[PDB]
Length: 378
Image 1 (cartoon, one colour):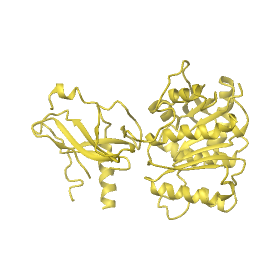
Image 2 (image 1 turned 120 degrees about the vertical axis):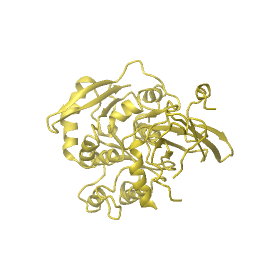
Image 3 (image 1 turned 30 degrees about the vertical axis):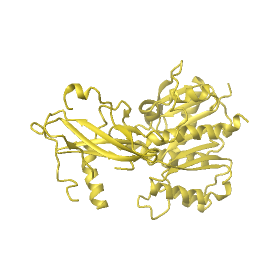
Image 4 (image 1 turned 30 degrees about the horizontal axis):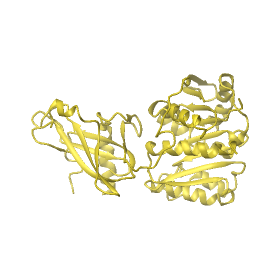
């Protein structure tokens, strides 16, 4: 234990079934500084998305930090560690202290170095994957298949938006188009290639054209994704025409899909409500329908505009998902779904297990694709 040979056997979190309902989970992190003798580190916080003031304890004399918890056998989520020299944060045995505490700590957050399923997702730091044995199946992800031909990455320099961004085109005639917001994530952090391939070879999905649009960065994303017509006009007038020349796709709206999570989810619906001629199928997960009111005591502007009949959602088929571990987001979505009582029949309302977490979304992204394209098989 602790000796370089002991660390060789470690591959991230280890769990042990303690129940039909529960597992006991242990986390290890190795201190690059050594024992408590030469180490700056006073805490190593385990930050579990949705679950979460609990620190690893060092095994004295060792460079081994360890922590043990319990997670129900159907839990899936992301987590990170925060090794730190602060021992004043979270020393006391409120909700406001927490957010301030974590605001102060999260910059030092790292992914689990021994867990290969890590990536750059979240606010601005690495996280790692934790799936329990009874966690819900995620179509495609449970059995990935690498493609023969790779996705084509281009630079889309926008005349109207006056910026450049990466775009990924991936195909799998008369093929449906699918636009995925936050494309850099689905192309690079959790590449969807092998997943869409698998599912296509299994006739869960139709041979299709996928366009993954780079959000560039948090600022651009925060301006371009929430209810911004210029972004979508640019997409339709500049980007889609360019994709047509590289990979021909169908011009039926009833099979053209826009897919996004949070701001992306908001944007997808936005694109649907306003340009149904182009976008007939809407995939929204954990949509940020509170926008722009952060407090959540006033309804999002999108909902307001529906209510006021300034925009309408017919000629649309919509998957609308939200998690229970994301209360504020769930409420916003429930209120939106409420307002949408009239097209209740063309909406797949899905209220899922997880939280505000890309590890969870990736499953519902695929399922939502299967759902919106199903009529193509009938």
